[PDB]
Image (spheres, helix red, strand yellow):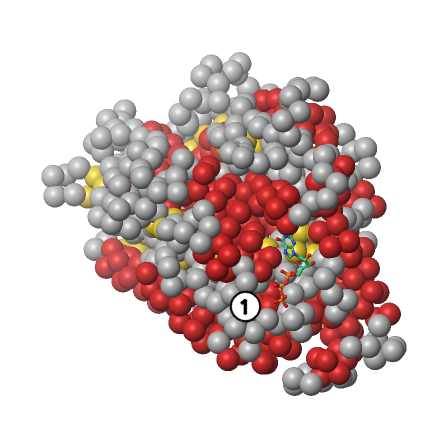
Amino acid sequence: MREIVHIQAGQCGNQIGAKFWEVISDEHGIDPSGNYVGDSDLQLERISVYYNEASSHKYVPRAILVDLEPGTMDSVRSGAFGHLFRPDNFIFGQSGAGNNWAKGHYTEGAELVDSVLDVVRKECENCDCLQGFQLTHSLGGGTGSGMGTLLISKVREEYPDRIMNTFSVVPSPKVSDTVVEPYNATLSIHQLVENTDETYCIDNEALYDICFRTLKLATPTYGDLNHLVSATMSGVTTSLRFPGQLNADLRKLAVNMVPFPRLHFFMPGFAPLTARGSQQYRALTVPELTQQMFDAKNMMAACDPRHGRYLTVATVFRGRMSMKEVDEQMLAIQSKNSSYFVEWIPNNVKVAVCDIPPRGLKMSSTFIGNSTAIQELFKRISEQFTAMFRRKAFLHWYTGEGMDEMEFTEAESNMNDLVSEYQQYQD
Amino acid sequence: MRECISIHVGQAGVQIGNACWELYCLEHGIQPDGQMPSDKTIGGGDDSFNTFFSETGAGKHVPRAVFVDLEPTVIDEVRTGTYRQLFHPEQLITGKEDAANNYARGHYTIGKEIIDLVLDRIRKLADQCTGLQGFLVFHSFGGGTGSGFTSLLMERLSVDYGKKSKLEFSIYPAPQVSTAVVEPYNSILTTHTTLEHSDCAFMVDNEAIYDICRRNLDIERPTYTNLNRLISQIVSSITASLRFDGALNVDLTEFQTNLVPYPRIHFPLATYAPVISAEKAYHEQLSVAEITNACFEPANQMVKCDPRHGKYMACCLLYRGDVVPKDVNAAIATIKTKRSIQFVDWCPTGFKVGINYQPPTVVPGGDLAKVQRAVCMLSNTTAIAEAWARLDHKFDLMYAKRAFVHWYVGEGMEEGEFSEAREDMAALEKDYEEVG
Ligand SMILES: COc1ccc(C[C@@H]2NC(=O)/C=C/C[C@@H]([C@H](C)[C@H]3O[C@@H]3c3ccccc3)OC(=O)[C@H](CC(C)C)OC(=O)[C@H](C)CNC2=O)cc1Cl
Ligand SMILES: Nc1nc2c(ncn2[C@@H]2O[C@H](COP(=O)(O)OP(=O)(O)OP(=O)(O)O)[C@@H](O)[C@H]2O)c(=O)[nH]1
Ligand SMILES: Nc1nc2c(ncn2[C@@H]2O[C@H](COP(=O)(O)OP(=O)(O)O)[C@@H](O)[C@H]2O)c(=O)[nH]1
């Protein structure tokens, strides 16, 4: 039972992670009090990886929540699992998360992260075995990225023989405002690349473009985003939570998935996307499910995979259907869409099936891809930063608290390097 | 708790300080005694107005601010005025020799021999307070005091307090009330030595205010009383955000962030719609949409410039009383319909809005007509180029004839230094020209 320590920080990170944890607990059926009220014994067979044990035999999920605005538990209790997290490790800041990198990444907050690292180190050893670390946040500026990549650097320092993972969200100038973020993102990911190899780029722009246009919305609120993300990035780890064919561990997930030590930006999707409606819907069929699988609109990234090629694909079906027939349409897709995949990497279709269905849904399937497609999103975020770097806007605070211009230029150089790598490996 | 300190240098500065401070004391329900609004009456308040006034034992709400000039002409003239006991006696400094329109006089002759006392007093005042945020500067370009002493003082402040922001309320000078022809010289000599220390500056234009007091306020010979009262009203209409409640543009840092892209360029335009004159009873009525759409008109723009011919960079507003957001958004949408306004090609340029729950308070015995609606646009329009280039042109006309140079030279300036400053501000004009 290789346990996982969950790291989590930031206003958006906590918002997404609360609903994610609620979804996973509900699917596993443990009561919001913290006791097993599930409906079978296939739940607690090895699930200690996410849920530890208390003295009174009640379970206890392990996940750290930190920030720099003092009120987090005041906002963490906004759902249904406030006291559920152990009530001694809600380390809180003092100021807030203005969109200022290095205001958490160099001087203040960095003072707090030493104690944070001490606490997480103390937290880790109690388990029987360690799997690694995985982190949920957004690349959003304002203590959201600083603390994130900072703690990434120190955890990678302390445990080189484990695996990182980021559930970060790329900001976008369609849903949001306070436009200094391109700096924050394109600078933090600049060392996220060297510091981590396991990433999911849930494009907020794509989430809006699919949630407001063709999902019957008028003003997408933050809970609206939280529904879709707490669906997809909660179903992404069912393979970890549930035994099955592709039980691959973090290290093994990587070795099956990441060819090169940098080209590791997975772009996920989820075929039965659903806005918040209590009624489930009419039923869907397996070929329809696996066809909405590659729905370009369905993609949680900013591209249509038809416009590019894949490298290493996974898939996790869920429900009760034809177990052994899924290979038929897997090979059908392979045969009719050879151009979509690449010849450099044969048999890039690792597939598996999980018996359990999700909450409020019978037939569904979480998806993971790895394609050249995210070159489009990176070109977007690179132009949406370079077209404004010429005016040197707002770099006063950054240049005052400990950055410099050469750092900005070298970050742009690194990201042009990544887009070049994607381009050439597409060529 | 938080707090802020407003400095007052120069005759014009201290006149506007008296007018503004009396208006502010009136507005909050405070009185020339400051008995009590509704609070603990000793170390009370707890609303935003405490950031200006602090209660003594009597709950007097003493305004922790000082007034400075180099001649006991005006300082005393108001020290025995209406607010004799409002401020602390022996907390208003009086110089001896007037700077006499000589920038070097305030920079290396007399202000340099007294600035230590001012520094001691302001540092003691800061020790008295606990929640200092920054500084509010009331000075003028033309005067020797309000330029040289201003620059040297703020240099000392930036040396010792290198973190807090600061806001400058200067007065752009006009020929029609000009009391010198060395006025562009002092203006350049001070402003060329501000950017390195200045954070944001609200400069007001004498000719603009004069045209406001006449063409709409029904005056023909406005004294310093009329112009000063009107500019005190507009300054209150600006700072009401800091005065009352959490809304758009609460903090000085928030001010500059919402306003200042690039540190060198921190001169934002300002407007305030109600300039309706006086006891003239009623020719029409008021409306939120009316005043909001008429705000864009060049009528009330604090400094004479042509905004419609220049690309914008941001837009903030503020409203007094009669709150309802819906018609405010409707008015924004109506004015949003891109008649000729433009914006920045690389960032969102929304019309940020923060409303306030109190109608404007008018002086009990003055010209302004009571109203209840208001707007206050702190537009960061690039079109202040025109005015700066006009002042620079008026400057370099008189440099081929080496006019008046010796007068500044005699106290420790340099002749070629003026050329360096002129090139600095030619480059600043180029910087405005860059945005296109
Ligand atoms: C053309 O100029 C413009 C002016 C305004 C706008 C819109 C305007 N803003 C920006 O894109 C400016 C971003 C900068 C950023 C700088 C680079 C980071 O170090 C900052 C910092 C943070 C905390 C403490 C100390 C320093 O600051 C800020 O984080 C603050 C927020 C608060 C905390 C003051 O600023 C805003 O965001 C304001 C208040 C919210 N509103 C806006 O949507 C657009 C343009 Cl293009
Ligand atoms: N609006 C307004 N402008 C004023 C007032 N007093 C002076 N000015 C203008 O400010 C500029 C110069 O300021 P002054 O007050 O004359 O000069 P000073 O600061 O006393 O400087 P010195 O005479 O050198 O000590 C001129 O353009 C004046 O017309 C006033 O009360 N209100
Ligand atoms: N995906 C997602 N993005 C959000 C949410 N709320 C805000 N955002 C945007 O994504 C970024 C959030 O990260 P961050 O800036 O660290 O949030 P902060 O801690 O509130 O400053 C910001 O640029 C926001 O504009 C949310 O609930 N989900």
Position of residue A105 relative to residue B228, above or below, is below
Q: Is residue A242 visible?
A: no
Residue displayed at 61% across by 35% down? B367
For the C terminus of chain A, the image quarter is: bottom right
Residue displayed at 23% across by 59% down? A122
Left or right: residue A72 compared with residue B309: left
Give the structural element (helix, strand or loop) at label 1. Answer: loop
Residue displayed at 64% across by 38% down? B272
Q: Position of residue A312 (x, y in %)?
A: 58, 49
Image quarter of residue B425: bottom right
Q: Position of residue B422 (x, y in %)?
A: 77, 73
Q: Amino acid at mark 1?
A: Glu
Ligand 2 closer than 8 Å to label 1 CB: yes
Position of residue B269 relative to residue B286, above or below, is below
Image quarter of residue A415: bottom right
Left or right: residue A395 compared with residue A248: right
